[PDB]
């Protein structure tokens, strides 16, 4: 078997966003270079609203 | 100890036909299975040990067959008739039965006397007894060779004493040997000395930690004189005025005094002076006090310069500069030793130099160090010739410290406190150095020269606390050598000697194992995989049943917490490719001899390299000496039959042959394999045949079934058996005639000589030449 | 052929393939041209330092 | 034929670490003073860790070297060449790296090898030959049944996904075709719409 | 190495059906394998205990 858990089921996807979303959901099964944690931000600007 | 073998292990048997026409002498040394496709030499090694046990030559021995004799009733005959070996009466009975068949007259009295007197015992010039008996050729060759090998280690008692005179200490009462033992005494001793360096060099941290721990436990129990600290403290308080109301530097020194760890420090002191390079460490407080300076000064003055490394020496100088010169560690971090020495000397501090201890030579040769001179350092850096410190200006330096101004421009509080403290330490070391010098010399005699120059304090377990160091010299205790303590050391010397001898044997065994089993490694996966699997197989076998290596080695290898199997596997791995010389022992020589004969003379042990399958209608030359009917034995496998060379096929080719039916019609020789065979010689007459069919054909391959000959003696004028041989047997199997078989006519070829040592010799179990003083 | 393919790969940095002549790869090209330069000063220097 | 780095920087010829002054270097750390004003026993503590790490690596380097060779034998040649193009960097927590070397498990594969033959690895590699036959047969069968493809409406993802469902219906008797077709799509579709275009190409 | 012989009947009157197409792994291999490499590596480690 090529994969213990498939990265994504091709039939379920519909566009490019579902591929990205599914890959994030199944990333725990794979050997990840960097294990995700809380994200750190260095820049944030809020624009004026209507 | 030595074993006295009473009887010579002859292996001869007599086989004779019922009618008595044919008789033969056969030497039975057993049958040993041999496997093809793997090295024969390695198999011969396993069988050599089993053969040695069968003959009784595995362990050291001396023959004691001199007394196995009797004297004839005739008054002329004064010869001694040996009872060992095949009895000459058995040959006489066999010979007379042969003459009865041929209707010849029986052996005459003169012929009987010559035959019955063949086996004799006679003395030689050196007093040894020589036994001439009927015995097998290989039994005689193997037994006599083992005798010469064991005799190399049997020496006279006076020769043994001369080899060990240099190692005998003066404080032991000499042993009085009996007069018989001086003249006729002999000892079986192996005098080869095996190096412990292969174990020490490979595993330095484990070896050093094991021996340091054992030594520390012994030194920690030495009795010491019980002297109170009140006299020393009272003098210090008077010299540097100590007030309950005020706070002084002297108090910080006094409240920190403790003798709890005194036995541990005094064992470290012995260790520094007992080994060539035993380096000790010392860690001071983050903010140095007057105790740290006093402790650091004591380390530089009363400890060998060989025990203090340059980095520790710089650290000691840095601590003094921080306290005395009012500077920080960051400033003195980059300063060198020469720069630091100038800073302290400008301020008036002269104790900035390490001092080398004076070496003292041991009176006797150290154990396991033949032709070598031992050494050890005198404690507390006191020159034995002058009976004072190496520094001749120590009195002047202490006075200079007293008038110095440290940590304060006005007053001499720090200088007076250190000067008074240092005077006390100088006096205690002057009075009590002799007791420590005797203690160091006693423990130096336990270790060899190899351990003296190799062991190092790699781990750093033995580090002296600053409070323990300054309290050690201020409250130095005189060493008292109790009688109980002295006897304890003598017991340790015996155990140390046994441990070293055990380790030497294990190292020699491991070095032999590595050379025979493992080759060299390559930068390939196949080589690494092959080495890893072979390494595990050897380790599993050596630790199975009774382990090859002793518990003493396992203690050294497991000192770091690893398992015994794991520790041995790592050490064997490093030994691959070693250039260490290994002395060849008598038992190794004996085994190589039996292995050589096993390969050279295969017919004695039941296997052969070549067999021949031939149709019955083809006539082949055979061995007719023994009178066998349809003898399966040929003097040599014929090169040509009917004017054509006999075809030879390797076993591998014959296994894969699919045209085997055409080949067998002509006949062929099978080789490139080891053929195990057995035979039975029956006294009656019958058809000589094989137990099983010669060959088995399968869809996978062809093979030869196990070979077992039923051999019968031949009566020529028997029509029934002649017809059955030609018509009921189609194919015959021939092998070279076994060399163990010997016709009865050649019974004089069984005569062999065995020499047994003189009976006047007495063997000494304990050859030591001294007694304990008490 | 395993021992020879094993050594040819180290020498030529390429796996031998059938129907292609085995000449030694780039290593043979460098050695042959460097030999010519050693013999005569008129021979060109055409091997890069890389 | 391939090549791999021996684990833990140990030369099999010398059976030791590549650095020939390692023992001298560790002894230098043991006797050194690093933070005298603000630290205690930094040199001794660090030195003790280094000896433990050195002993474990020298003890267990053969087991990990054999393990790497066992894993390399499972990958077919075609897969290895494609994996050469990709690249990556692995971030290891400092606690995990030290814990790996401090407690280095012993790996023994003696029971796996029968002489020099690893039965499990040899049988696993042989299954790729079966997969090669299925890939070629499935691609030819789809080409003949469907021919050139057109996309008058719908996205590329919908075009490829619905084609796989039709392949399932047409070849329901032979389920191997759809399974092999979906195996290629799973690897291709990770890139997204670009990967789906490669699958149709 | 050589094959083992069948029965005599099968050698005289025996017929077998065989296919000669070995195929290739290139269609599955030829792709951008950056995303699926991690999932493949996880399965590779699990093959050997």
Image: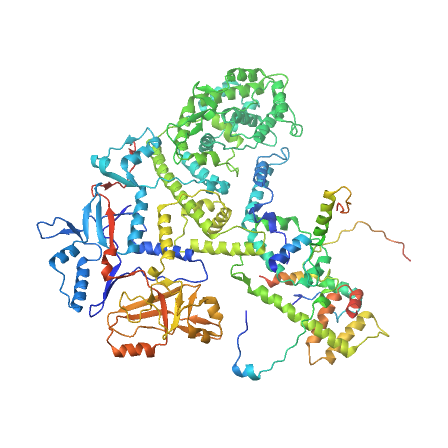
The foreground one among D40 and B113 is B113
**In the picture shown, does residue B636 fall above or below B180?**
below
Q: Assign the C terminus of chain D to one quadrant of the image.
A: bottom right
Q: Residue at x 68, y 75 (%)?
A: D176
Q: Return the x and y of residue B709 as percentages of the image width and height.
A: 32, 70
Colour scheme of the rendered structure? rainbow
B378 or B753, which is in the foreground? B753
Please tell me which residue is depicted at 24% across the width and 50% down the height of the picture: B753
**B243 lies left or right of B331:** left
Q: Residue at the far left: name it.
A: B75
- Residue D157's image quarter? bottom right
Q: Position of residue B145 (x, y in %)?
A: 31, 49
Q: Quadrant of the N terminus of chain D?
A: bottom right
E5 vs B598: above or below: below
Viewer can see residue D99: no
- Residue farthest right in this picture: A50
Eyeballing the image, is B47 above or below B289? below
Image-quadrant location for residue B177: top left
Farthest residue to the front: give it.
B643
- Residue B364 in the image: state x and y as whole percent: 37, 29
Q: Position of residue B392 (x, y in %)?
A: 50, 17
Q: Residue at position x 13%, y 55% from top?
A: B113
Whether residue B72 is visible, yes or no, is: yes
C20 versus B660 height, above or below: above
Q: Is residue B653 left or right of residue B721?
A: right
Q: How many marks?
A: 0
């Amino acid at each position: 078997k090529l994969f213990e858990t498939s990265p994504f089921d091709p039939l379920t996807i519909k566009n490019n966003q579902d591929v990205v979303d599914k890959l994030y959901a199944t990333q725990s099964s794979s050997i990840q270079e960097v294990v995700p944690t809380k994200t750190f931000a260095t820049e944030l600007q809020f624009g004026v609203t209507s | 100890e030595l074993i006295k073998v009473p009887t010579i292990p002859h292996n001869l048997v007599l086989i004779q036909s019922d009618n008595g026409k044919h008789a033969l002498i056969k030497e039975d040394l057993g049958q040993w299975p041999v496997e093809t496709g793997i090295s024969l030499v390695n198999q011969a090694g396993v069988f050599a040990v089993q053969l040695a046990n069968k003959l009784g030559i595995d362990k050291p021995f001396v023959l004691d067959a001199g007394s196995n004799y009797f004297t004839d009733t005739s008054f002329i005959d004064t010869r001694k008739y040996c009872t060992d070996g095949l009895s000459p009466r058995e040959i006489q009975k066999a010979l007379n039965r042969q003459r009865a068949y041929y209707d010849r007259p029986e052996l005459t009295i003169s012929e009987n006397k010559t035959l019955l007197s063949q086996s004799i015992i006679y003395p030689d010039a050196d007093g040894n007894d020589v036994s001439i008996i009927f015995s097998g050729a290989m039994s005689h060759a193997i037994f006599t060779y083992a005798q010469s090998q064991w005799n190399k280690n049997i020496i006279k008692l006076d020769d043994y004493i001369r080899e060990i005179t240099l190692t005998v200490p003066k404080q032991y009462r000499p042993r009085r040997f009996k007069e018989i033992e001086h003249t006729h005494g002999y000892v079986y001793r192996e005098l080869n000395q095996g190096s412990l360096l292969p174990l020490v060099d490979a595993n330095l941290k484990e070896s050093s930690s094991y021996y340091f721990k054992k030594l520390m436990s012994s030194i920690s129990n030495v009795p010491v004189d019980a002297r109170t600290l009140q006299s020393a403290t009272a003098a210090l308080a008077a010299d540097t005025g100590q007030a309950v109301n005020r706070a002084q530097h002297v108090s910080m020194l006094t409240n920190r005094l403790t003798t709890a760890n005194a036995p541990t420090v005094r064992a470290i002191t012995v260790l520094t002076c007992m080994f060539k390079q035993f380096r000790i460490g010392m860690t001071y407080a983050l903010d140095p006090n007057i105790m740290d300076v006093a402790a650091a000064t004591c380390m530089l003055l009363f400890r060998p310069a060989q025990s203090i490394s340059d980095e520790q020496y710089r650290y000691c100088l840095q601590t003094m500069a921080v306290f005395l010169t009012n500077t920080t560690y960051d400033i003195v971090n980059n300063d060198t030793i020469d720069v630091l020495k100038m800073k302290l000397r400008n301020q008036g501090w002269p104790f900035v130099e390490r001092y080398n201890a004076v070496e003292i030579d041991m009176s006797v040769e150290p154990l396991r160090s033949p032709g070598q001179v031992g050494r050890y350092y005198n404690p507390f850096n006191i020159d034995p010739l002058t009976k004072k410190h190496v520094e001749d200006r120590l009195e002047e330096f202490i006075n200079q410290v007293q008038v110095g101004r440290f940590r304060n421009a006005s007053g001499n509080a720090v200088g007076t406190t250190l000067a008074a403290f240092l005077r006390a330490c100088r006096d205690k070391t002057s009075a009590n150095w002799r007791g420590y010098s005797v203690l160091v010399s006693r423990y130096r005699s336990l270790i060899p020269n190899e351990l003296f120059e190799s062991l190092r304090n790699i781990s750093g377990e033995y580090n002296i606390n600053p409070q323990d160091e300054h309290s050690f010299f201020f409250a130095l205790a005189q060493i008292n050598a109790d009688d109980e303590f002295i006897g304890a050391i003598d017991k340790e010397s015996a155990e140390y000697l046994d441990e070293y001898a055990t380790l030497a044997r294990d190292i020699s065994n491991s070095l032999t194992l590595v050379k025979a089993a493992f080759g060299p490694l390559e930068r390939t996966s196949g080589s690494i995989i092959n080495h890893a699997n072979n390494l595990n197989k050897v380790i599993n076998h050596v630790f199975a049943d009774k382990p090859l290596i002793s518990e003493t080695m396992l203690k050294i290898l497991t000192i770091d917490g690893t398992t015994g199997k794991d520790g041995y596997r790592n050490w064997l791995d490093k030994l691959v490719g070693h250039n260490y010389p290994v002395y060849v022992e008598p038992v190794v020589n004996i085994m190589n001899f039996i292995s050589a004969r096993f390969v050279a003379d295969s017919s004695y042990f039941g296997y052969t390299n070549e067999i021949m399958i031939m149709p019955n209608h083809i006539n082949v030359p055979v061995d007719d000496r023994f009178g066998f009917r349809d003898s399966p034995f040929c003097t040599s496998l014929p090169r040509t039959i009917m004017g054509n060379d006999v075809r030879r096929i390797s076993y591998n080719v014959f296994s894969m042959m699919e045209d085997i039916d055409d080949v067998i019609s002509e006949g062929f020789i099978l080789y490139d394999a080891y053929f195990n065979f057995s035979y039975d010689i029956m006294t009656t007459d019958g058809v000589t045949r094989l137990k099983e069919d010669i060959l088995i054909v399968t869809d996978t391959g062809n093979d030869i079934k196990p070979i077992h000959f039923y051999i019968y003696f031949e009566n020529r004028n028997d029509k029934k058996l002649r017809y059955e041989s030609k018509m009921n047997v189609s194919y015959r199997l021939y092998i070279k005639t076994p060399a163990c078989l010997l016709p009865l006519s050649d019974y004089m070829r069984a005569q062999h000589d065995y020499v047994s040592p003189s009976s006047s010799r007495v063997y000494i179990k304990d050859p030591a030449v001294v007694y304990t003083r008490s | 052929d395993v021992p020879f393919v094993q050594a040819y790969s180290k020498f030529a940095d390429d796996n031998p393939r059938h129907l292609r002549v085995k000449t030694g790869g780039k290593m043979a090209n460098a050695l042959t041209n460097v030999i010519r330069s050693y013999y005569s000063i008129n021979a060109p220097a055409i091997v890069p330092q890389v």
